[PDB]
Image 1 (cartoon, helix red, strand yellow):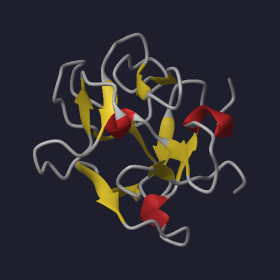
Image 2: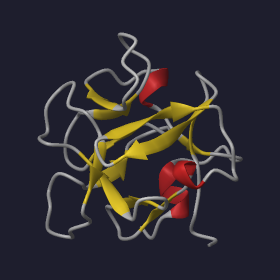
Image 3: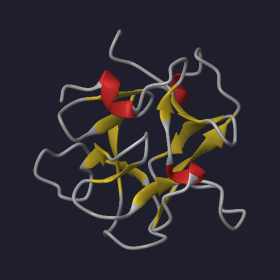
Length: 134
């Protein structure tokens, strides 16, 4: 598709990688790897192409793991949004899509808003929403 993209963190030089419904980590960026492909399927949901499941969290808490859930427009736990300067996080909360703290391989929700909570569409200087609908 054209809506498809890789989620990139400039500081680590790595892209998000869907390993399984309960596991979403990072890997060296490869535009040909299905597991690294995602796409917005609505104004607030991003779906992993390889799994046809939407990025989400069990609850809106600090250090909650970001994994894959059956896409559901009504779930308030799989809704994301773009903050300022590529900072990305859960819609309506000050918790960010984060990677890099504590040797934790899975994507986590984190309170910090530094370089590790900022993501861009691989191949651009744009935030994730540039590939979205809103």
